Image: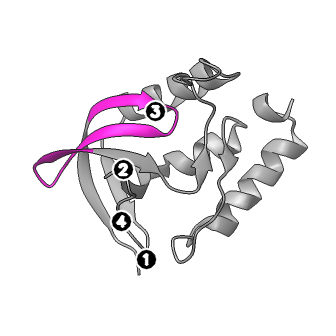
Amino acid sequence: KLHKEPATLIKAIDGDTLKLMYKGQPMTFRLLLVDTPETKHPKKGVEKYGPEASAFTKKMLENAKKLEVEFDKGQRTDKYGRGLAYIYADGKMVNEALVRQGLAKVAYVYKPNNTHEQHLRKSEAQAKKEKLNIWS
C-alpha cells in the first residue's frame, strides 16, 4: 500500500517537474504517469499549452495548505536523479488534475510504477470527450 509523506514547495519548474523540500533535502520531482507540454524545449521551445500547464501546476501547488508526495511501488528516482511520484495538493492529486483538464497526456507506463494508471486513463478519456485544451 502506497503512503503519502509531507513535502514543502521550493519551486515549480514547469507542468510536470518541480523542486520540493523532502525529508530535509531539496530534490527535483517528476510527476508520474503524465506528460505536459514543454516550455523549455531546446528543440521547439514553448510547446502549445506548455505555459498553461505550467501555470496550473504552479498555482495549484502555491495555493495549497498541504503538499504530500506519494511514491509508487517501483523505482523512486529516474536516471536523472528525479524523484518519481504522485503529488497531492490538499488531498487532490496534481497528476490527475492536469490530465482531467486536458493539460497533460498519460505517459508511457512502466510497471510496476503504474498503480494509478487506470484512474488517470479514466480522467484522460473524459477530458478528451469534453475536448479540453490539448484535446480541442
The magenta stretch spans residue 22: yes
Coordinates of residue 126 in the picture (x, y in percent): 81, 49
Q: Looking at the image, is mark 1 or mark 3 earlier in the sequence?
A: 3
Query: What label sits on residue 80 in the rendered view?
Result: 2
Given this view, does label 1 or label 2 mark the residue nearer the observer?
Answer: 2
Q: Main secondary structure of the magenta part?
A: strand
Instruction: Estimate the spatial distance between the alpha carbons at disc 1 and disc 2, rounded to whole Å.
Output: 19 Å
In this rendering, is residue 17 above or below 31? above
Q: Is the residue marked by circle 4 packed among few (<14), some (14-19), or many (20+) residues within 10 Å?
A: some
Pick whichever, 60 or 46, lies toward us: 46
Task: Check disc 4 and report its element: helix, strand or loop.
Answer: loop
Q: Amino acid at mark 3?
A: Met
Instruction: Estimate the spatial distance between the alpha carbons at disc 3 and disc 2, rounded to whole Å.
Output: 25 Å
Residue linked to disc 4? 76
Q: How many marks?
A: 4
Instruction: Estimate the spatial distance between the alpha carbons at disc 1 and disc 3, rounded to whole Å.
Output: 25 Å
Give the residue at x 89% y 45%: 129
Q: Amino acid at mark 1?
A: Lys
The stretch in magenta equals: 10-27
Q: Looking at the image, is mark 1 or mark 2 earlier in the sequence?
A: 1
Residue linked to disc 3? 60
